[PDB]
Image (cartoon, rainbow, N blue to C red; front, side, top):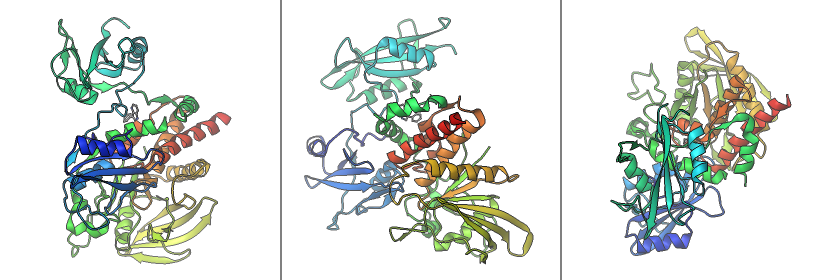
Length: 502
Ligand SMILES: c1ccc(-c2c[nH]c3cccnc23)cc1
């Protein structure tokens, strides 16, 4: 499903692959070898290869002569279902027809590379469960692989670990007979669908990879130390899982809602979008905002885009309807001379009407990294609906990449948390940047992780990529870059240290 991404290939290897194994319309994507956030889409057209740059500074994937996207899987799905839409600098059309599959197993959750049968047995015994499995290098037979599978009752002998040898002959893979596969992923997927049955009848069911990302929070420093010499590899394994999250976005794709999206292809999932009720009867579609509910799976969030001039009223309808009392803004209104969010709040001491809502800015307070605006929101014609909405406007995030130190963000998020916790029956905390996925996702995931450690103290289990995957199932592309991914680990580490210091 995401086999067109080749994590460890060079430009010339990509060219030769497309020229010898592909046809016109063949394509693949790959990282830049030294440049994080740069990717290349390599495509074959008229017997030649073209390389198309995709940049991601933290907000979205920006395809040259194409559009902006929330994930590379969403980018490929869009253009595979939309020909004539990707053009060269000269205007000529670049068709993405045939993904060119990668055989490299390194971003599979189940692939552990160098590892002994004894090490894999203890890992499967301590962490594993029925159907927990891994693939590793053989050591006895160089170039071969072993599949190790735990099967049993959930140390009393009711469970066991089997080792199935996997031969590699002609760069095809087999388990001793039957089909020979072009890759270990194809072998795993096959024996996931069609499990091996032993002679005495044990079914070697490959239910889940062994979890290697879950850590005890107290031991965060050791995991970060280990990832710092990696973070790229762990991030790319997470990114491989995004092909499971192509959920429908049909409401955002409606003609009627086109001009309510900051970026035409960055859309909320139908199953978690905020639906706005009590709309204008004369506006035929008034139930739409580019926003999703994010539930940790007590505090929930709405992840949304920066307002457009035509969505400011809808934004306030959302805040009112959802009973939100805290907004987190993670962008300046303008960065690099581009508008990222329209000003949707009044100047200090001023009162403005936004459709049927009225907002007073009571007071602003400037801190180093942020401005707090104390806002009063009510429905026009109904005085007893007034509530305070506290807008925390983070002002010092760099235009590209992440802050060099997480202290400013953590102090900000602590103040947000206490504000939210002090307000009886407050609704979800609204979080927004520009597209509402990169910074927004980073702030939300840090908030969710810190909240676990707040309830359960320094001795609790956290699992960063599992948390991100769960949030990504609720809005597209939450947490955009490897730099945000590392920043998340650094923020949790700093949080833990300040608590051990105390
Ligand atoms: C859910 C849980 C874990 C992961 C995961 C991200 N990087 C990984 C490296 C090795 C194994 N698993 C992972 C992704 C989704």
